[PDB]
Amino acid sequence: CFEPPPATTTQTGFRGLSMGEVLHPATVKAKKERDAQYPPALAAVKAEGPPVSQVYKNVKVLGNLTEAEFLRTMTAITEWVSPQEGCTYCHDENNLASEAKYPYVVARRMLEMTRAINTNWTQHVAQTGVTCYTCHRGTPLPPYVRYLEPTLPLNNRETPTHVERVETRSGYVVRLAKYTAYSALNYDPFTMFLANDKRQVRVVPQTALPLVGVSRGKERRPLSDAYATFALMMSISDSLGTNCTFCHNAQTFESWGKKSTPQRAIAWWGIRMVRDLNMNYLAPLNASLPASRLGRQGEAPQADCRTCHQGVTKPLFGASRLKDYPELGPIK
Amino acid sequence: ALLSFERKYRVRGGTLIGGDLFDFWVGPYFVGFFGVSAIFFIFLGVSLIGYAASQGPTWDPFAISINPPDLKYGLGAAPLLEGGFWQAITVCALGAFISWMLREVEISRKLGIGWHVPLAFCVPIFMFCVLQVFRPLLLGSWGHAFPYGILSHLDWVNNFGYQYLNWHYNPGHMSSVSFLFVNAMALGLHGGLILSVANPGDGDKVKTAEHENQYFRDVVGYSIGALSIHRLGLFLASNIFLTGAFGTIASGPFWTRGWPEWWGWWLDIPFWS
Amino acid sequence: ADYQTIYTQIQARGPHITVSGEWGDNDRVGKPFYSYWLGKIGDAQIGPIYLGASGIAAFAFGSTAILIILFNMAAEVHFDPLQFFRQFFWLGLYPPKAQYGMGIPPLHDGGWWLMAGLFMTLSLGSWWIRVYSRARALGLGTHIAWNFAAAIFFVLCIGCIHPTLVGSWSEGVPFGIWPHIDWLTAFSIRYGNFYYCPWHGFSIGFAYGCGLLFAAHGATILAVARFGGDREIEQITDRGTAVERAALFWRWTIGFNATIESVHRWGWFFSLMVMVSASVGILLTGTFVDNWYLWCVKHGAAPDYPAYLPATPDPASLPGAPK
Amino acid sequence: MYHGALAQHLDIAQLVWYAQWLVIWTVVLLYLRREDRREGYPLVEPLGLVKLAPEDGQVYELPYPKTFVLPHGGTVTVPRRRPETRELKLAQTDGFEGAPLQPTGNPLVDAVGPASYAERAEVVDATVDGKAKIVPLRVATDFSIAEGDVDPRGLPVVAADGVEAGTVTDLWVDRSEHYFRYLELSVAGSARTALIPLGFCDVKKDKIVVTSILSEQFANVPRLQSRDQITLREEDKVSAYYAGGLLYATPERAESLL
Ligand code: BCB
Ligand code: BCB
Ligand code: BCB
Ligand SMILES: C/C=C1/c2cc3[nH]c4c(c3C)C(=O)[C@H](C(=O)OC)c4c3nc(cc4[nH]c(cc(n2)[C@@H]1C)c(C(C)=O)c4C)[C@@H](C)[C@@H]3CCC(=O)OC/C=C(\C)CCC[C@H](C)CCC[C@@H](C)CCCC(C)C
Ligand SMILES: C/C=C1/c2cc3[nH]c4c(c3C)C(=O)[C@H](C(=O)OC)c4c3nc(cc4[nH]c(cc(n2)[C@@H]1C)c(C(C)=O)c4C)[C@@H](C)[C@@H]3CCC(=O)OC/C=C(\C)CCC[C@H](C)CCC[C@H](C)CCCC(C)C
Ligand SMILES: CC(C)=CCC/C(C)=C/CC/C(C)=C/CC/C(C)=C/CC/C(C)=C/CC/C(C)=C/CC/C(C)=C/CC1=C(C)C(=O)c2ccccc2C1=O
Ligand code: HEM
Ligand code: HEM
Ligand code: HEM
Ligand code: HEM
Ligand SMILES: CC(C)=CCC/C(C)=C/C=C/C(C)=C/C=C/C(C)=C/C=C\C=C(C)\C=C\C=C(/C)CC/C=C(\C)CCCC(C)C
Ligand SMILES: CCNc1nc(Cl)nc(N[C@@](C)(C#N)CC)n1
Ligand SMILES: CCCCCCCCCCCC[N+](C)(C)[O-]
Ligand SMILES: CCCCCCCCCCCC[N+](C)(C)[O-]
Ligand SMILES: [Fe+2]
């Protein structure tokens, strides 16, 4: 179990602090090649005549698009989400306004979510933006998703061993470790931190001395919180295929300013963004999904940092189609 | 000036190099050629430290830091204030340490005793090289080395560790810590026991070699022996760094992921996956 | 070259020796037996061993503790054997995940951990008694029992006393291989970085120092084995060239020197102090110091550096930033 | 308000830092550094023509004397004044006290430099039960060589100069520690045995190679007064002899190694 040099290294810190990335070229290149499959933008069409709000029968989101654009969007969508399945993955073969199949109405919500991210989570996704491809990677079910309990393999395009199967209790500690970069942290960062906004990530105190009245007995947060926060940060690390010094000077994890990189503020936004998507878009979809889709507690599959990033500090190495398909936002 | 018993030992000879020229003592210190190089370098190193530290802001001892260059200067010479000092101070350090070491050999020779202490001292010098020379060479920049500052060299250890997510699971480190901890226990055991025998308390008779053996046969079922417990400790201490050196070297040049994942080789045997 | 300092060129066999203690000579169970290979780099006789009461006591409590841990560990892989053997390192028996203050946790959330905690404690005690008694039985000083007490106390600090002092059991050390290691980071992160704890520094200083000292002492003795330097007891009561040469080695190198007894004192003290410094460092943590970095910063100690990537403000503090 | 806060900018952990330092320098300087001076003090020196004071600091740097009560009787008190009465065949090579001394005769027999012994007791080191501790296997009859090792009795001893210098006759064993410590050989062409500490022996299957001294120089290896017994001080004389071979067996040995 080893990885032959050279190693690609960068600097994220004042010299002598040993801060920065540490990359094995073959892996980086293997990820580059995978992320290279991002289909190119379909050719630009000329906007002719009538907003499909007039033209078509059941168009709610993309209603201001002229036809030609609209069908370019529909082709792009098909190319990103359901390439194998073709247009009828979502449409009635003989009625295109029909909402008969759930992918139609899920897709409709996913056009709104996608446009939200690009319009409202600028502080994360900036001018790169996401498209459906970012998560779906050419399949209807996106490869990395999270249920309300750790599952395995992380790539759901792989087949579980018995142990891996969520039903096999003996496989729990492993299902959990493999989600926290192989640690034995007995916590699930996902349901603790990412599924919603219940829990506070910061544990470290901000005064030298213990403030009287939050520092004894049931006043105190339990050490277990610190474990959880370590668990979450191990997960973020593995999700972005990087290490703590991508964001922190370990001198003081808790301090900002010179003691943190730009990417930590971007990360701080991403946690918030993920909670929005989970609470307000993805988790509700259990209303609309086949039971075939749902976790053991009837939860829709939802998202974490892996769902977009898939092992890369910027998903798809920063590939963008934001300017190619503005239907998807930033929406004025 | 001289211990009660010293004079009979202060004879010429034993030099590695130089012979009679520096073969003499200043106070208690033997000089010899390497004592002279030692001093030359110490004075250099310490001078650069002060000249460099004066260019910096702080004079507070805990805060002063002389760091290496940016990774960009690679393995080349860096401007004085931006790593230049650090590269020079490192060279003085090695000069100092190795002179110290060779000097011990000459003292050993002159007293007709084995050279085991200068040998034992090679280990720390080695580990200093693994951290400051070998690993930076393998990774291709002096920038990866550690800064010369009482506290700052800790911030380096801290980050270096967390670059690999949890440095604790580093099998080299695990082995390294294990020797640090036994060695410490055994030094307590071996000292306590020698004192326990020579200092029985009240007015009891000093005890015997046969006692030493009995105590550990009684307590833990095995006594290693008087000569051997010194051969063990030299061994336990030495392997703190000799095994550790592997965990340090593997990190980057041979493993770029978190260290917990390395244990994948076990956890992921497909037989029990 | 002195091959004896590497290994024993010709090994002597001869009748088994017993030194009688003020009691318990009847409790030495087992028959001495002799290993050739062991003989090469050590005494060749393994065993016999004193049984004794505090010994039997320590074995019995120790084992109880081990069963509680191992059962709770087997519950984790749902009593699947192979997965047990597979996941063993990752398996653990944790303190309360929830804040019960100082209240006795439920079995399922730390109850079992406190159990094992208590038993291991009793195990440690009965063993201290054995370590102390055998010296007294054999008419020896108790310096070893006193070095050991310091180590037990450290553990009592991290397992009990600090949890009690701040008032939460959730802070204790879980039993398990990876789990006890995970704690180290959790504890450091909650306390603002143990690198900046002045007692962690003293501890390490002595820990390194023990390495420094046992390598210098071990080697010094091998290096005068020729003059029988290894018979340290009689080199104390009647100084010989072994330790005159040992002393002058060190006087000529660093300028001052120990004696063959005093050096063992230096060692004992250095070993002791690793555990003493660590405990003070823990007794102050949470009780009186919350963030060791900031405490350092409050006092002028901490280094600080130029930014290299742009200084990044807390988004959370921004105008209009969410929660 | 804060736990630990004592006063303006003063707090518990910070006072404890100061105590910890103190406790360390106290134990180190005032205890350990004085335990180190139980042997060899006070320092010896040239003599002053007119001097009259119990020099103040020679008092202050010493511990109070301690007495060891020895197991088979007597006692020993340290520190205590233990001057080297024995005459030394060494000559000052230059003026300053820095200067090394030179042997004026045969330092091996003169016993100087690497060839020095300590003034140990002229007493036979004893086992716990009162017997002589280091004794030849001729005497130590319940002892043996472990099956597997070389029995050197009969093997030739070959000296630094490649010349067979005698014939191993016996091993002496440490009955307290069950451990061999010297070999006895019949010196070649002399009517004498010599002991040689097992550390100066390279023990082959077919010969015992000793590199400290030339075959000539065994003739003057220190003699025991008994034949089945050896004193603490004799052990030192025997051991020092070969040890001094290393600097002195030949003229080039003391000179610059390279
Ligand atoms: C978050 C980061 C962490 C970290 C990061 C870390 C790193 C990055 C490395 C270690 C290494 C090591 N760590 Mg870990 N560590 C250790 C213990 C240890 C050491 C046994 C080992 C080797 C130390 C070394 O290189 O000395 C170096 C000693 C030197 C260089 C001695 C030089 C002396 C020179 C010869 C002479 C100097 C002379 C002076 C200038 C003279 C002054 C003059 C005056 C005195 C007169 C413990 C016990 C713990 C615990 C309990 O948590 C721990 C936690 C952690 N370590 C953290 C998890 N550790 C090292 C290793 O071996 O692991 C593989 C290593 O590379
Ligand atoms: C890979 C891990 C590393 C590590 C990890 C480590 C940790 C984590 C800690 C220390 C600590 C300490 N380290 Mg560091 N270290 C130090 C020196 C020091 C001291 C400042 C201090 C206590 C050392 C000690 O007592 O040991 C035992 C030695 C003894 C008893 C003999 C006395 C030696 C003396 C105390 C050293 C003092 C030297 C001066 C500070 C240096 C300047 C000398 C010149 C300029 C005259 C040197 C000189 C080196 C070199 C030459 O390699 C080194 C390498 C490293 N340290 C590695 C990079 N060290 C502790 C500290 O508190 O730092 C703030 C601590 O917490
Ligand atoms: C990221 C986390 C960090 C961390 C966190 C940490 C914590 C939280 C603590 C330490 C502590 C300590 N650390 Mg640090 N650390 C250390 C070194 C050390 C030690 C000197 C000291 C622990 C004392 C000890 O010997 O425990 C090993 C010895 C023990 C456990 C004694 C055992 C006694 C017992 C009688 C034996 C058991 C007997 C039986 C076998 C029991 C079995 C019975 C059954 C029934 C269970 C180094 C050298 C480094 C380096 C090189 O970077 C480092 C970095 C760091 N530490 C990181 C900054 N460190 C401790 C301390 O000193 O803080 C003040 C402490 O509490
Ligand atoms: C595994 C075995 C180990 C081991 C072994 C042995 N250890 C030995 C011996 C043996 C056998 C000796 O024979 C020799 C000695 O004589 O003992 C008294 C020695 C010695 N072990 C010292 C320090 C020590 N051992 C450490 C570790 C271990 N030792 C491990 C544990 C540590 C740790 C862990 O931090 C330290 C700091 C010195 C006191 C002494 C060298 C003096 C010197 O070389 O004088 C000559 C040099 C100087 C007086 C100063 C030179 C200053 C340079 C030019 C400028 C500073 C350089 C810069 C790099 C500093 C940065 C500081 C910054 C990080 C804050
Ligand atoms: C700075 C100084 C230090 C220091 C000092 C000292 N350290 C000492 C002493 C001193 C001086 C002693 O005198 C004492 C001792 O005696 O040594 C010879 C001891 C010790 N330090 C041990 C371990 C150690 N020290 C560590 C650390 C440091 N130490 C630090 C560094 C660490 C670290 C590194 O983490 C470790 C792990 C043990 C070997 C030993 C205690 C055993 C015990 O307390 O017993 C407790 C009793 C038991 C475990 C009983 C159960 C065992 C059985 C086999 C389980 C069987 C299960 C089965 C199911 C049963 C079937 C039954 C059948 C009939 C059906
Ligand atoms: C002055 C001048 C300009 C001179 C030219 C000559 C010259 C080169 C002088 C040297 C100048 C210098 C730079 C001196 C500094 C030397 C140094 C590096 C001293 C370090 C002191 C330290 C920190 C030691 C740490 C370990 C420690 C705490 C030791 C104390 C205990 C002792 C004394 C251990 C040594 C020791 C050991 C290990 C034994 O086993 C032993 C066995 C039997 C008898 C004695 C001993 C004994 O003395
Ligand atoms: C594949 C190329 C493809 C075709 C063809 C296509 C066409 C299409 C049309 C003409 C409409 C408008 C019909 C009407 O009047 O209501 C339309 C609308 C939506 N589509 Fe579509 N579509 C194709 C593929 C896909 C795929 C693969 C999906 C599901 C992932 C999908 C979904 C939808 C949704 C939702 C709408 C509503 C648009 C809105 O703005 O509300 N289509 N499609
Ligand atoms: C982009 C506009 C976009 C479309 C189109 C889209 C469609 C879509 C469908 C058809 C489903 C249902 C699939 C099924 O068979 O159940 C679906 C489900 C999920 N999506 Fe999606 N999706 C679009 C964009 C995005 C983006 C940007 C992400 C990731 C942040 C994302 C994620 C998911 C997840 C999670 C689900 C639910 C789980 C599931 O049903 O498989 N989608 N998407
Ligand atoms: C690498 C495994 C790693 C560690 C360790 C780590 C720790 C850590 C802590 C202790 C906190 C708490 C801060 C406090 O208590 O005030 C914390 C918080 C954040 N981190 Fe982190 N962190 C590690 C890695 C990473 C990585 C790789 C990034 C950047 C992509 C990152 C980011 C953040 C952010 C953002 C926070 C704040 C959370 C919030 O405010 O809600 N960390 N980290
Ligand atoms: C999950 C909470 C999460 C983390 C953590 C995270 C981090 C992160 C960082 C550090 C950056 C910037 C890296 C850099 O500037 O070098 C970044 C950037 C983007 N992210 Fe992200 N991110 C998290 C979650 C998510 C999710 C779920 C998505 C996709 C819907 C997503 C997307 C993006 C995009 C787009 C970017 C790139 C911005 C750019 O400048 O290219 N992230 N993320
Ligand atoms: C108020 C009350 C009621 C009580 C007072 C509190 C009390 C005294 C509690 C004490 C708490 C203490 C002592 C807690 C300390 C915890 C600490 C220090 C734990 C440290 C380390 C734990 C470790 C490494 C645990 C490891 C355990 C094991 C590996 C199990 C051993 C297994 C074997 C022997 C069999 C191997 C099986 C294999 C073949 C598959
Ligand atoms: C003569 C001294 N013997 C001796 N001394 C010591 Cl410190 N330990 C041991 N034995 C072990 C098993 C223990 N405890 C450590 C190897 N024997
Ligand atoms: C608190 C630790 C366990 C206490 C009980 C242990 C049994 C005590 C045995 C003591 C025997 C007495 N002796 C001979 C050592 O003095
Ligand atoms: C980091 C722990 C503190 C280490 C303590 C170091 C003690 C060194 C003692 C040397 C003092 C020598 N002398 C001659 C001045 O006494
Ligand atoms: Fe010793």
Image (cartoon, coloured by chain):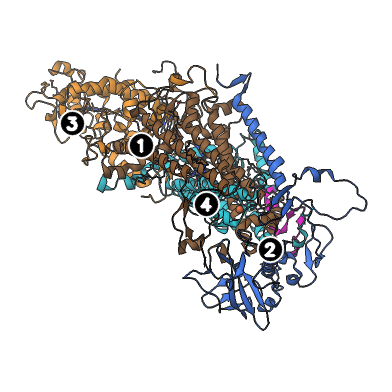
Q: Is mark 4 within 8 Å of ligand 12?
A: yes
Which chain: orange?
A
Q: Is residue C266 magenta?
A: no
Q: Is mark 3 within 8 Å of ligand 7?
A: yes
In the image, residue B266 sits, relative to residue A233, either above or below, namely below
Residue B226: which quarter of the image?
bottom right
In the image, residue B3 sits, relative to residue A158, either above or below, namely below
Whether residue C31 is visible: yes
The amino acid type of the residue labelled 2 equals: Leu
Give chain D's shade.
blue
C-alpha separation, residue under disc 4 versus residue under disc 1: 30 Å
The amino acid type of the residue labelled 1 equals: Ile
The amino acid type of the residue labelled 4 equals: Phe
Q: Which residue is mark 1?
A: C68
The mark lying in front, picked from 4 and 1, is 4
Q: Which residue is mark 4?
A: B216
Q: Which residue is mark 2?
A: D232
The amino acid type of the residue labelled 3 equals: Thr
C-alpha separation, residue under disc 1 versus residue under disc 3: 57 Å
Q: Residues within 10 Å of mark 1 (few under 14, many from 20)?
A: some
C-alpha separation, residue under disc 4 versus residue under disc 3: 77 Å
Decide: marks 4, 3 in contact (CB < 8 A)? no
